[PDB]
Image: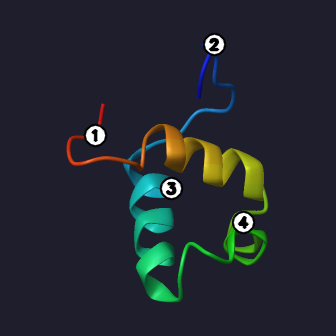
Amino acid sequence: GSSGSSGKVKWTHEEDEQLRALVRQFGQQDWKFLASHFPNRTDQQCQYRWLRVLSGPSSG
């Protein structure tokens, strides 16, 4: 990030957990694929929500 703040699409302990596991599952490296798991979500939203939420020692 840099300037601005705004994140669309909602996320619950479900997706987060899913994506979280999905990451370790094979590797976050392949988001385009991970997003596949989520027909409602996408690589961007995923990666984003990750690099936005699922990113750091303390989830904020």
How packed mark 4 is, by other alpha carbons closer than 10 Å (few <14, some 14-19, many 20 or more), is many
The one nearer the camera, 2 or 26, is 2
Q: Which residue is mark 1?
A: 59
Q: Which residue is mark 4?
A: 35
The amino acid type of the residue labelled 1 equals: Ser
Judge depth for marks 3 and 4 and give the one in front: 4
Q: Between label 3 and label 1, give the one nearer the viewer.
A: 1
Q: Amino acid at mark 2?
A: Ser
Disc 3 residue type? Glu
Q: Is residue 41 above or below residue 1?
A: below
- Give me the residue at 53% from left, 89% from top: 26
- Pointer 3 and pointer 1: residues touching (CB < 8 Å)? no
Mark 3 highlights which residue?
15
Mark 2 and mark 1 in contact? Answer it, CB < 8 Å.
Answer: no
Instruction: Decide which of tag 2 and tag 1 comes sooner along the chain.
Output: 2
Q: Say what secondary structure mark 3 lies in.
A: helix
Instruction: First in sequence, mark 3 or 4: give its number.
Output: 3
Where is residue 59 drawn, in percent x and y?
Answer: 28, 40
Residue at the (53%, 82%) spot, across then down = 27
Whether residue 25 is situated above or below residue 2 in the rendered picture: below
Cα–Cα gap, marks 2 and 1: 20 Å
Kindly state the secondary structure of the residue where label 1 is placed. Answer: loop
Q: Upstream in the sequence, badge 4 or badge 1?
A: 4
Q: In terms of secondary structure, where does tag 2 sit? A: loop
Residue at the extreme bottom: 26
| Residue nearer the viewer, 44 or 1 | 1
Mark pair 3, 2: CA separation: 26 Å
